[PDB]
Length: 229
RNA sequence: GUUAAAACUCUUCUCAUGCUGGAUUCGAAAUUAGGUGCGCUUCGCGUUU
Ligand SMILES: [Zn+2]
Image 1 (cartoon, rainbow, N blue to C red):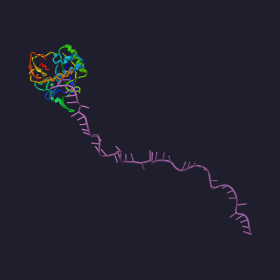
Image 2 (cartoon, rainbow, N blue to C red; image 1 turned 45 degrees about the vertical axis):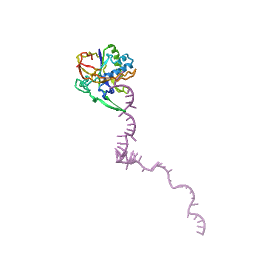
Image 3 (tube, rainbow, N blue to C red; image 1 turned 120 degrees about the vertical axis):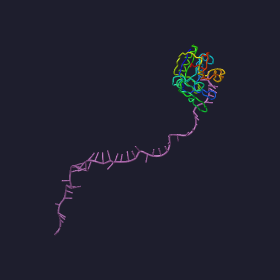
Image 4 (tube, protein in one colour; image 1 turned 30 degrees about the vertical axis):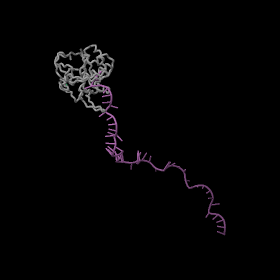
């Protein structure tokens, strides 16, 4: 097991809508998965076939959680929309969003300059050979996460491709960094599969668990995530 | 293989109006149209009582 670390920053702003006209503050790992699968199909890579597999259970993408001037990731504030890093507060929040009115199109973005965590957890080392190639393409051109990729919104640039290994969590009690798939969890989560080869945009809805919640689970390996805490 | 994809903050509107490169100072200070050359040459106040 290993992971590729990164201080992924935004060249142009990203627009990710949620339900209830909510715009997400930071970019999520689902968006990274959806973009990297387009990369692997576009470069005729084999893992693209696994990219259209939503339960491959290797190459799991952790959320692009924002990084602070404290050098640490903003830990998500428990049961709250905004985030707060363990060192100081520096609290992210909505102020970073801007209401956009552009040619009829009224939407929102999140501004550029803030840095976000790259963390691609990979299990199979055979997949790491293609993983080095896809992080090496982004290294040259960039990745686009958001809406209006063809208009140019969402351009991301890595500044630190680091393939440093890691180990899973220890405590059973873990904090939910990202929203987790837990049935009858009363926190509705929506994403989609596009399947551009065969069309049929999906808009898959679910009722998983929300982020910022301490939960005890001995059967935990750590799209939810496990914070060691 | 991103609750996607698709949609150019676009159109209209002259940095314009008002203000003179003007005021002061003389082309005049120095220099004699001067120097050379003879109105000369020729002809008796005759004749007549
Ligand atoms: Zn901080």
